[PDB]
Image (cartoon, rainbow over the protein chains, first blue to last red):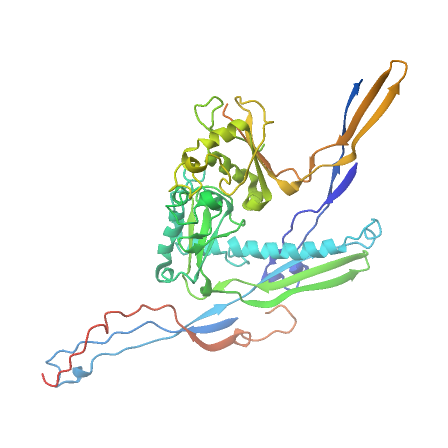
Length: 51
Length: 253
Length: 151
Length: 43
């Protein structure tokens, strides 16, 4: 088996109000992401004869 | 805030009678004028992300560049989405919202289910609502959704070579200029449904981007929890001079 | 779920036309906007039906490459045509064409084609063996659209 | 701003007034001067 990796999608930011210009909400929200993986394999094919 | 002055409208002269040559009425009437003003503002966009100092060791490869790139690309996605169809509550009013609130939302006969496609003639018919600014073609921008483009690719009026020059669809499979308007495809249009926009035409020179500070990255170390917070902020807005210069077409109700 | 059930009948009441083939690009979604990265494959019957297509007959309709002057179909809606004979038999609900995103597919392989010979003196026989190990896989779960005859 | 401990009195010290003057697109004049003159020195 061979395994690869898959990058996640895109996030987004937020628009803060003016009333929170001094508090701890002035940095808005948080963006998060996780990776993913895929797999590969093979099958066997054969044939024979006699003389 | 920033303020500029808008010059007033025009005036009229008078046709004096022939019996008023010997009186002060010979000199005519008065022309008065008063200036006005407009203002511009800005809005703040922010995002953050944390990375504890133990997941960095608790893995084989690094995870910081992914974090930073995700931050920046999320910021760009949000700003472009807001410019597309942001409302007015603390965020810039989107182009489609401007067109709708200016009564420039032309309700066409194309159907959202798929019974009737979107024809190039329908797209070109939107130029009427632009009024005086629609006469010039070098000063316009056309943007269509993905599904509008795919329905354009199957237009009965662009198939034959004899119908449309050398740019027939059958020979190319691609659509370039529609009625002289270059075609640009964007996927950030709203969901396809009844009464939803699928193409917009804007007067490019009428819109500006007020901006206070660019995208800035700040790094804070929170030793009390052993993390590495990152902060990204910017202040922008989308503003226009006058109350015209956009038209949007929508599916039928 | 990319099997598009088109209107072409499985007997011959309705033929397979160029519009049916070109309409499949929509179900490719974002991948369908670039023609240079696609491959079209049609069966025997599909190709013979295309040869009788009504919209490729005249010089006025389609340039100089009208069917009446050449008798074969080359580029169709910008897509080059490849004919393959291994499609299933013409029947209701079966397929006749496919478009694939070429770069989305890989062919993993462990060993090449190898031949080994064995001598069985007890039977006066020579046994020949040919073996190989391959497979067909894709990166992400999309990029393929197939059209099928009507039910 | 009115968020810090020290702020300014009135908005006029938070605003930039510009003398730049702008006008919209105006109508054009066509039949005003397309005919030919006829000078009269009498009534």
